[PDB]
């Protein structure tokens, strides 16, 4: 629990956060963990006097003991520069902390109010062309440029991690060079499942499959009165939506028809935590049958299936190996 | 990143039973070389402390100014108490043609090119305030368009 | 959320006498019955709803709310409201520069906390009788003043107020810092400092309670979210 | 990149990552049979005293 | 009509290296470049608004070796001319024959260049020009005449220049000893430390 490159011997004075009282032989002892963000969190508090006077609160902290660093600093209607109150002229309250108990690349990232800019202004030190915030699953899309991408990515994704951690939510970098290509793909190559929803014809499908037909993936919740501005009538199609629900029920029956409900044997691979029936079928399609057979497979061997990712295959292999090794314990 | 200019420092007195207690007032002004400006007026028994106080004051309660490139957007008058101030946008190269306290505020604001006269009083504190007011009131073309319900090309 | 009928029952529609009014409250006034100003409930309700919504939103992002009411009639009630949604409050006299001068008041708070600790957790006792008494008095003073805001830590992210004219100092402070204000504003009061004005009877107890309760509920909802 | 980094980390820590395979575990056992690597050691970062900078 | 005294003193006063000596030997070795001249050098209180401007003006004047009236005239000319005033002034200064020569590398210092110009060494478009203030135009070839081409000083100067960065706005030939003033220099091509704006302001009192 030490620092990065910061190495030295006897006589070197350095502070350390202590909270691990472990009793040993002939009296109890105590250890220190001076490498967490808390130590560097109050580091600015000791320097910046505004932080102690409730003038600049820290939303979150995301530094790298031995690498770079990024913290939160947003004033409460005091109309005062957030980073300007800790730097101003010849910011001596930034370099000091940077090379305090560990030479870290501290990058104070000021926050705004809107959630779109909540991360747009957290790209510093870099620019921002746009933003693709996904308010649903744990996914994001940093929309900047290749020039700043390297500075926005860093080395092992420290910047991304720091940013995401500082923001509190998710944050993933991406390219915007194919902005006129992905758009057509999302409304061109992803338009793929309209015939299954709204009943169509081969001609309408065949010129609307390899290029996308139409319909509305659950688009009935959106206002369909704007489709009345287009030519034609669409009075009965809502009933077809109900037919889609019926098809969904059949799809639900299919969701259980997968290999006659996973045949009947194995049961070890099917009852594994973190894997569904489709994921178990995709994993077992490569010759595996039991959880031990899934543990025998590697991340590269499970990477042949596009349904599983390298991190997900690694987590599944680790879970199967833990179930095999710790099977003696309940 | 912020630049800060102490405009003036003045010794002020308070008479008491013993005699005169002296103190010092520091008028400063700070800016980021873009729209943001803020003046601060600090007071203390010793000069440096006073100056520091002024600086602190300045750093909070800043104000934004719409700048068309290096200069102002149109001729603007600003008044405060005795000091009434006129300042007029000017062509690249001309520099800040302005006197005293007024100059300092302009410089920090990141106006590079102005023609500016201070009529009336030239009491630094008042004149800086006046200047600030002038800057503040000054609207941009975009802003005006927004106000009027038009495009920028309609206004020219 | 809060209905009009309920409000009427409470006595929200009643205002102050016509000679004590503010002409900036002329939009929110309906008429004058028996030489006493009647607040327009048609204009009030939507505004109130909006305010509530805002509060809820604030809560949702883990916002700190401060409940201010130093009338002494609705001091008991405001505290209760605060405690229901585990938020902070100032039910006794607002200390001039509580928020603007937080850093000084933070010391006071700390002192109070220390005193409390001494009283409770220490269990030392054995103190000189006069000195002990003095200490107790001090503790009492602190509790009265800063009891609700002792766990606030920093500054609040919104400020709910029961009377704008009475708590103008607080309101002013909130404006200087830029904290959103949610004031109940009778006809005599000034709405210009207030961000989310609520035209309603500050004085009547039942009305005040009603105002509190809904707000509390909304805060709770936000928290849940 | 160096086997000293493999000796710096424990075998249990490597077994808790699925990047290594079942045959890779047997190869690691065959390498550790010579007892030159993966003996459960702890280094400063890289360098021993004999590994000194000159 | 010229400053004939100690050159490094001026530099010291300014603060910067003005390039008033050839650059064989570094300026820090020749003089206390940080310390100001005279008995009261070590003392350095912050200057006034007027004073800084004045200093700036001096620096520029010193660099080129232009006395005050001439400088004023130049400024006036710049003002008269279209475009940015300070920039114009700078361009004008550059345009001086001696300065051009120095840039080319036929003089070790600007002073040397000036001297050369005076002594009928330099020709502009094959016509002997003797005036240091002569404003050299675009596409005006400027050369050493055949009499002065044998001088050891000239070659030394050239060598010095070669060590020094080459200006983009000229094109010089070391063997032929003739350079073409291709165009009047852009502000970006010149040194960034010179605050022309201050100078402009000073004269706009």
Image (cartoon, rainbow, N blue to C red):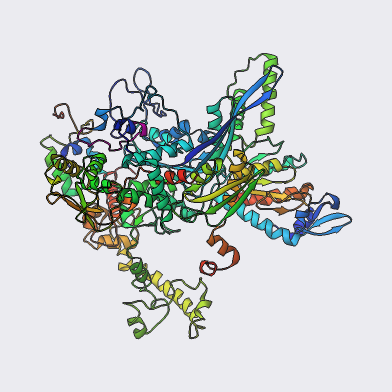
**Foreground of the two, E96 or E56:** E96
Q: Is residue A107 visible?
A: yes
Q: Is residue B64 visible?
A: no
* Residue C37: quarter of image: bottom right
Image mark count = 0
Query: Which residue is depicted at the point 10% across and 36% down?
Result: D34
Please state the extent of the stretch shown in magenta in the rendering: E12-25
**Foreground of the two, A187 or C113:** A187
Query: Which residue is depicted at the point 46% across and 49% down?
Result: B95
* Furthest residue toward right: C34
Query: Which residue is depicted at the point 69% across and 32% down?
Result: C144
**Foreground of the two, E17 or A245:** E17
Asked if the stretch drawn in magenta spans residue A87, the answer is: no
Residue C60 screen position, x and y as percent: 55, 51
Residue E198 screen position, x and y as percent: 43, 43
Residue E195 screen position, x and y as percent: 39, 44
Residue D2 is left or right of residue E132, and the answer is left
Is residue A24 positioned above or below A275 on the image?
Answer: above
Residue C186 screen position, x and y as percent: 76, 51
Residue D3 is left or right of residue C103, and the answer is left
Query: Which residue is depicted at the point 50% across and 83% down?
Result: A234
Is residue E189 positioned above or below A189 on the image?
Answer: above
């Amino acid at each position: 629990d030490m620092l990065p490159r910061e190495n030295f011997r006897p006589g070197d004075r350095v502070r350390g956060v202590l909270y691990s009282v472990r009793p040993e032989a002939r009296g109890a002892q105590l250890f220190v963990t001076r490498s967490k963000p808390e130590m560097l969190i109050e580091l600015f508090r000791i320097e910046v006097p505004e932080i102690g006077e409730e003038v600049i609160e820290i939303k979150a902290a995301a530094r790298d003991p031995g690498s770079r660093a990024k913290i939160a600093v947003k004033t409460n209607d005091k109309r005062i520069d957030p980073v300007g109150a800790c730097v101003g002229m010849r910011g001596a309250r930034v370099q000091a902390v940077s090379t305090e108990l560990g030479g870290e690349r501290i990058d104070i990232v000021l926050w705004d109010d809107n959630p779109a800019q909540f991360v747009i202004n957290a790209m510093a030190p870099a620019d921002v062309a746009s933003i693709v915030v996904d308010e649903d699953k744990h996914t994001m899309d940093i929309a900047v440029e290749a020039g700043n991408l390297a500075q926005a990515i860093g080395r092992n994704g420290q910047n991304v991690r720091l940013a995401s951690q500082l923001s509190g939510w998710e944050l993933n970098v991406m390219t915007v060079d194919d902005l006129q290509a992905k758009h057509q793909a999302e409304a061109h190559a992803a338009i793929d499942t309209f015939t299954k929803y709204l009943d169509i014809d081969e001609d309408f499908a065949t010129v609307l499959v390899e290029e996308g037909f139409s319909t509305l993936e659950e688009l009935a919740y959106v206002p369909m009165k704007e489709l009345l501005e287009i030519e034609g009538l669409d009075e009965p199609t809502v009933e077809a939506l109900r037919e889609r629900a019926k098809n969904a029920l059949a799809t639900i029956a299919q969701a259980q028809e997968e290999s006659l409900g996973d045949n009947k044997p194995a049961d070890d691979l099917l009852n594994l935590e973190g894997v569904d029936r489709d994921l178990a079928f995709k994993l077992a399609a490569r010759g595996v049958c039991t959880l031990e057979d899934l543990a025998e497979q590697g991340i590269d061997d499970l990477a042949d299936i596009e349904g599983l990712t390298d991190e997900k295959a690694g987590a599944l292999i680790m879970a199967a190996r833990n179930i095999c090794w710790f099977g003696d314990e309940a | 990143e912020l630049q800060e200019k102490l405009i003036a420092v003045n010794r002020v007195s308070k008479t008491v039973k013993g005699g005169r207690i002296f103190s010092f007032t520091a008028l400063t002004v700070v800016g980021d070389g873009n729209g943001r400006v803020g003046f601060g007026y600090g007071k203390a028994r010793e000069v440096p402390a006073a100056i520091q106080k002024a600086m602190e004051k300045a750093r909070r309660n800043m104000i934004n100014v719409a700048l068309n490139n290096g200069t102002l957007q149109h001729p603007v008058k600003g008044v405060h108490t005795g000091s009434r101030v006129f300042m007029q946008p000017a062509s690249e190269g001309t520099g800040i043609i302005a006197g005293g306290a007024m100059r300092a505020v302009l410089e920090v604001a990141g106006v590079h090119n102005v023609l500016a006269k201070a009529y009336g009083s030239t009491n630094p504190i008042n004149v800086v305030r006046a200047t600030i007011d002038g800057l503040e009131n000054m609207n941009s073309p975009e802003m005006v368009a927004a106000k009027r319900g038009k495009s920028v090309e309609e206004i020219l | 959320t809060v209905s009009m009928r309920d409000m009427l029952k409470a006595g929200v529609h009643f205002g102050h006498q016509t000679r004590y009014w503010n002409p900036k409250m002329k939009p929110f006034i309906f008429g004058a019955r028996n030489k006493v100003h009647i607040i327009n409930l048609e204009k009030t309700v939507p505004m109130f709803n909006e305010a509530l919504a805002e509060l809820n939103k604030i809560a949702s992002r883990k916002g700190k709310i401060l409940f201010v009411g130093t009338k002494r009639a609705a001091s008991e009630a405001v505290k209760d409201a605060a405690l229901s949604c585990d938020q902070f409050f100032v039910n006794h006299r607002w200390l001039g520069g509580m928020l603007t001068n937080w850093k000084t008041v933070r010391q006071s708070i700390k002192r109070l906390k220390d005193l409390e600790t001494q009283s409770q957790d220490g269990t030392f006792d054995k103190l000189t009788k006069k000195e002990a008494l003095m200490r107790t008095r001090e503790l009492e003073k602190l509790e009265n003043s800063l009891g609700g805001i002792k766990d606030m830590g920093g500054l609040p992210d919104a400020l709910f107020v029961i009377d704008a004219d009475h708590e103008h100092i607080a309101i002013k402070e909130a404006n200087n810092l830029g904290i959103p204000v949610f004031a109940i504003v009778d006809t005599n009061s000034d709405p210009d400092g207030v961000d989310f004005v609520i035209p309603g009877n500050d004085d009547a107890i039942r009305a005040v309670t009603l105002y509190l309760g809904a707000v509390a509920a909304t805060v709770r909802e936000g928290r849940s979210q | 990149h160096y086997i000293g980094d493999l000796v710096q980390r424990t075998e249990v820590e490597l077994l808790k990552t699925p990047n290594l395979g079942k045959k890779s575990l047997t190869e690691i056992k065959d390498v550790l049979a010579s007892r030159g690597l993966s003996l459960g050691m702890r280094l400063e970062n890289w360098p021993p005293a004999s590994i000194a900078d000159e | 009509a010229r400053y004939l005294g100690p050159k490094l003193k001026l530099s010291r006063r300014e603060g910067t290296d003005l390039f008033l000596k050839s650059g064989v030997r570094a300026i820090d070795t020749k003089c206390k470049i940080e310390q100001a001249p005279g008995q009261h050098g070590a003392r350095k209180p912050r200057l006034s608004d007027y004073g800084v401007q004045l200093r700036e003006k001096q620096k520029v004047r010193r660099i080129y070796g232009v006395l005050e009236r001439q400088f004023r005239n130049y400024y006036k000319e710049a003002a008269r001319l279209k475009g940015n005033t300070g920039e114009n002034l700078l361009a004008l200064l550059e345009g001086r024959l001696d300065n051009v020569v120095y840039r080319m590398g036929f003089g070790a210092t600007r002073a040397e260049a000036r001297q050369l110009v005076s002594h009928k060494a330099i020709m502009v478009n094959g016509r002997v020009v003797n005036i240091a203030s002569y404003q050299v135009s675009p596409n005006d070839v400027v050369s050493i005449r055949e009499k002065a081409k044998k001088q050891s000083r000239v070659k030394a100067a050239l060598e010095l220049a070669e060590q020094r960065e080459k200006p983009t706005w000229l094109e010089v030939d070391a063997g032929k000893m003739e350079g073409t003033f291709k165009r009047k220099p852009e502000r970006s091509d010149l040194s960034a430390d010179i605050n022309e704006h201050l100078i402009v302001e000073l004269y706009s009192k």
